[PDB]
Image: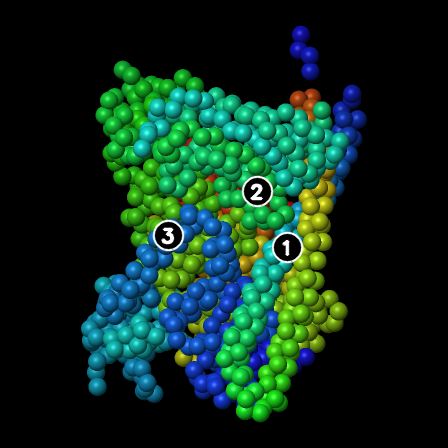
Amino acid sequence: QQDQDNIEAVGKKLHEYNTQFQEKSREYDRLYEDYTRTSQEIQMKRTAIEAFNETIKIFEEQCQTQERYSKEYIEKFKREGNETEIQRIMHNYEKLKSRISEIVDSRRRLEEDLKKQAAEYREIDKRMNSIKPDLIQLRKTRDQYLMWLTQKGVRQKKLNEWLG
Amino acid sequence: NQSVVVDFLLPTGVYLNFPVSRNANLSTIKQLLWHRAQYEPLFHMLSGPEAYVFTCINQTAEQQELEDEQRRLCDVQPFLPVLRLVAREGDRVKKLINSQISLLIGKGLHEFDSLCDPEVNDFRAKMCQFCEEAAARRQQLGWEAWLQYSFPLQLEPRALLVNVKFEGSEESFTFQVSTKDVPLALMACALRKPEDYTLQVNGRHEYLYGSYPLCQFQYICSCLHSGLTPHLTMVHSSSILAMRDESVSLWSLEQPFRIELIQGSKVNADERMKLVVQAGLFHGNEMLCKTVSSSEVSVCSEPVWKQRLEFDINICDLPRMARLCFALYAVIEDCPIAWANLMLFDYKDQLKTGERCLYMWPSVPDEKGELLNPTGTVRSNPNTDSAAALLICLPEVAPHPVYYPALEKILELGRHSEEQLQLREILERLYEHEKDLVWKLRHEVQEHFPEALARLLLVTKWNKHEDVAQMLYLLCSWPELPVLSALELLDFSFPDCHVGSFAIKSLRKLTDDELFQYLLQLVQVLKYESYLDCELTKFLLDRALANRKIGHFLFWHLRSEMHVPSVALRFGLILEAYCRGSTHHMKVLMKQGEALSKLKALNDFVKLSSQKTPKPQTKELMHLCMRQEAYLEALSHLQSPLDPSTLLAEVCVEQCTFMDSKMKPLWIMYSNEEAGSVGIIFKNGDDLRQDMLTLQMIQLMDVLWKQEGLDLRMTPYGCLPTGDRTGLIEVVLRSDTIANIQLDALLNWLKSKNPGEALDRAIEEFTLSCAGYCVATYVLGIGDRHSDNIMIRESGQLFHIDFGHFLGNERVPFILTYDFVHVIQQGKTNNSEKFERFRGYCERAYTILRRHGLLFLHLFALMRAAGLPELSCSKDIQYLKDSLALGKTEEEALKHFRVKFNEALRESWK
Ligand SMILES: C[C@@H]1C[C@H]1C(=O)N1CCN(c2cnc(C#N)c(-c3cnn(C)c3)n2)C[C@H]1C
């Protein structure tokens, strides 16, 4: 009316399924370290890029200043003969511009790494999501076999030696 | 490498690039800069050096005006070595504090602005105004009241001499005084060559004042029991002032609640399987209606559903704290992928409308394995760039926006609307029939059973708005409950704002001392909160601003979880608020934070070196790093994080070492010749939160025992999580592990450290402490107790360290160790008189903890917020019920304890 193997044989399988569980648990926990670690490394890159923007912003304010400030000034060095003081100002500005190119290049390099690390994150999260169903099924099997042997009346000491 | 090339942006647009030393302070770098700038164009147009401030992009990506030019470039620690000169003028008090807050709390303040969220902005506005106001108010008040704020009294729950002196004086006056002398009386006696003075325990920020005898103060109590003369300084009221300075109703929308499930984004699943979004509405833990599911759309990265999801609840029925919950699953024609929760009403009580993009949290496959996660946080995932997301849309209910009704209108539904024999049995000792029986007699529960409020809130049918109004009506006139009851009402089971407010109302009667015992649990409870502005946050802030110690430990409890995405935002905004009302204390916490950052750098070096090379060479190479200006000065002269009244003055590099654990803790020794040789352990690598809870609880037991006239000579030592797998332990000197003392031997060790008549004290100390830590470890279920993790003191006192596991994580028996029994009985085979006194201490101790059983159950129940591995469910809580036998009579419980005791004595032999 209610539709829903020897004890030693079911105990042998309880040993196996608990082992296969504990292996899979240790595996998922390794990935969850990587997930949490990489989540932190990505946030560090996401604010380091902000620090690159805010630096590159400040260098560009300097360029704006260099042009506004020199425009109203440099006409005096032209009419008063100093071609050399003009050329000093301009070289010093090309030296500024040249430096921005390094900072932009290093921002590009970081942006490349965070592109790679975002792909790693998603891959780690994907591999966790193909371990979850195995893990949960091994949990529930392990628990079914315990329930079976308990009902059959197996001593608590015997179940403990099978569990690890 | 020593030197770094720094880019210098002059205000004329000119650009200089030259190398400076990492150690060089900014004052010095400005001189070098000016010296090179004179040989660059447009120099004549600059003002003098002191007209300008350096500016850099700091480590948290914010601009920082570097006002303190005595700081080293390596401590300023800019992002790139780029320094800009700008003008000094502008309100740079606001600027300074905003910068200093960003570095102090971890998260930079721009990250709050960036979110473009009103809730955040209004919290930041209201709480910062509140905090700034209280600090302004604090400053105007007297030196007495300021001393109460800054250095609140450390009290304990015949006559000897005392060494008194004044500040700035070599001579010191010693004289006899009694235990029961109030502090002012001693000052009158000290005036021998009163109310414009206060005593200080020199070498420490601990002061003696108020109408309390000398024995009640911890410093005196500490010195008396030892048998030592206290050392004090008299300080003038003038000197403390030097310290002190520097329009349509919701109940007419009878149409079932529904949502449009548009899209999934950034999903990562097995392509053979197919995706299902499961969903449901919740109030606290209970379901408001049955859970509905989407169609099984095939696994891609960007799945599109576009389904209405009709729920079996009308929009009028939705309670204030309604909580829509999602879970994304991957099915084969079951893997939980992710989950996300959403509040249906916003912080302004408005029913949310329109599209909403929930960035989801990943599911963790747990033992319960539920469909949805209604306990989890409301906050979106901070990782908006990489995390999975659900695009959904809450429909337009009406042309006008609709709010959840105001209290005047809630109470208006209250204004419309033999049996006791069954009710007493149910409350005075719930299932289907009983829940109704309480609800019918809900008026009688308020009248004769006010303590049963909690039971009554759960029987309330929160998925029908008529019920909800009636419960709230009763609640508004509900009599004030004791603290113990109010603690239960902070638990997640009671999510409604009106319950929260009542709970906090009843907690305002907490003294600062008592509030300190629960501060950790109260912090964790904030993880259950829905909205940023809440009553608990204002309460915690109120008490932090009124008391510097509470403020201190509030700071560290929150700071030490700033790495946890789920709480980073909520905790950041509170830390910002605290700091703004405690600018005085910011400066102390800055110094600690930097000391902590050097230790982390220092530990990481020791970790790496000890793998390669042996201990004595690694010990000396550690010292080399510590000798460096930046290191030595940052580690020197700071108030201890573990207790801000303690003073870590001069770091003793020779005594400084590290221990042989897996994570290799650093052992840092200090010295202060005003005091007297304090030390600390810097643990980095393991979680310390579980050790703290265990110590907090043993300390609570010690307090609980002491109140009933039982001092069991415990050592309630400090333990403080400061960060991500990082914290401190207070060193307790003249103490080693039993394992090391053993390499018979315990009693020999006590003999050598307590010669003559002092040995009888040391056995009494051992007996008393062995009792407390036997009962404590039994009650908390702390197994794995061996001589490697138990410690004796030279005084005789036993205490416990490295509480790795607890609450049985199978039942832990009561444990008597032969070696300890031998020492208890004074080295004899049979000393029944002594061993009976020891049995009585255990039984007395155990009796008193049962009397306060619900307190332990309530405090533990709130710690389920923290999500520690070994405290996650009702089974963990149930352990304490059974260990304290709270479902038995007092004598029945005590007879089982005796059977546990006696069988532990039998088990001791083998
Ligand atoms: C100076 C010498 C290098 C250090 C060393 O190797 N020692 C042996 C072990 N030991 C420990 C170990 N763990 C803890 C903790 N946790 C404590 C401890 C001390 N006080 N408290 C509240 C805990 N003590 C004592 C120390 C002398």
Chain name for mark 2: B
Mark 1 touching mark 3, by CB under 8 A? no
- Amino acid carrying label 1: it is Ile
Whether residues under marks 1 and 2 lie with C-beta atoms below 8 angstroms apart, the answer is: no
Picture residue at 51% right of the left edge, 65% below the top: B62
- Whole-percent x and y of residue B45? 48, 86
| Mark linked to residue B540 | 3
Of labels 1 and 3, the one closer to you: 1
Report the side of B515 relative to B665 (left or right). Answer: left
Q: Amino acid at mark 3?
A: Leu
Q: Circle 3 sits in a helix, a strand or a loop, which is it? A: helix
- Which of the two residues, A156 or B246, is positioned nearer the viewer here? B246
The quarter in which the N terminus of chain B is drawn is: bottom right
User: Which residue corresponds to the image point at 42% horizontal and 26% vertical from the top-left?
Assistant: B315
Which residue is disc 1 drawn over?
A42
Q: Residue furthest top?
A: A1
Residue B278 in percent (x, y) is at: 58, 29
Q: CA distance from mark 1 to mark 2?
A: 16 Å
* C-alpha separation, residue under disc 3 versus residue under disc 2: 30 Å
Which image quadrant for residue A159? Answer: top right
